[PDB]
Amino acid sequence: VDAEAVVQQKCISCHGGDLTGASAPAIDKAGANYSEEEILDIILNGQGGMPGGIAKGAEAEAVAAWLAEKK
Ligand code: HEC
């Protein structure tokens, strides 16, 4: 699953187009701040106001890895 496409259609909804942090904090650099493990769990689980489980399996895996790679 195209990680950037996922993020660019599942996360930008709150994080904003560039993931610079609109209705949610900036995660374009979340790969710098946190590791794929952390991010993966957060995608699967949630964070604060984030519903979580927005992406799962290959979706969330691809997301987290790509996010780690975004850094
Ligand atoms: C709006 C309903 C959200 C969607 C859709 C996604 N996220 Fe999110 N995320 C959101 C918020 C508001 C927060 C922080 C808590 C708060 O209430 O302010 C987050 C947090 C994350 C984090 C951690 C960032 C941090 O806590 O500093 C990550 C790594 C993250 N979110 C990733 C992420 C991805 C990749 C999503 C799409 C699969 C996604 N989020 C959707 C709000 C929302």
Image: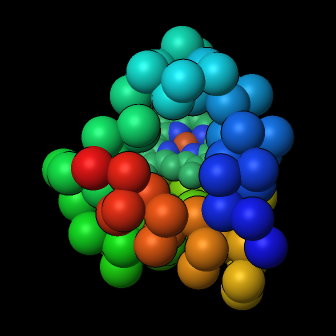
Q: Between residues 47 and 63, which one lies in front from this camera angle?
A: 63
Which residue is painted at 27% across and 50% down in the image? 71
Q: Which of 8 and 21 is in front in this view?
A: 8
Quadrant in which the N terminus appears = bottom right
Give the number of marks: 0
Q: Would residue 25 appear left or right of 43 to someone viewing this image?
A: left
Q: Is the residue 66 above or below the residue 60 in the image?
A: above
Question: Is residue 24 something one can see in this rendering?
Answer: no
* x 61%, y 20%: residue: 16
- In the displayed structure, 29 sits above or below 64; it is above
Identify which residue is drawn at 54% across, 24% down.
18
Q: Where is residue 56 in the image (x, y as percent from the top left)?
A: 73, 76
Residue 37 position, x and y percent, is: 36, 79
Observer-nearest of 19 and 45 = 19
Which picture quadrant has residue 62? bottom right
The x, y position of residue 21, in whole percent, is: 46, 20
Q: In which quarter of the image is residue 6?
A: bottom right
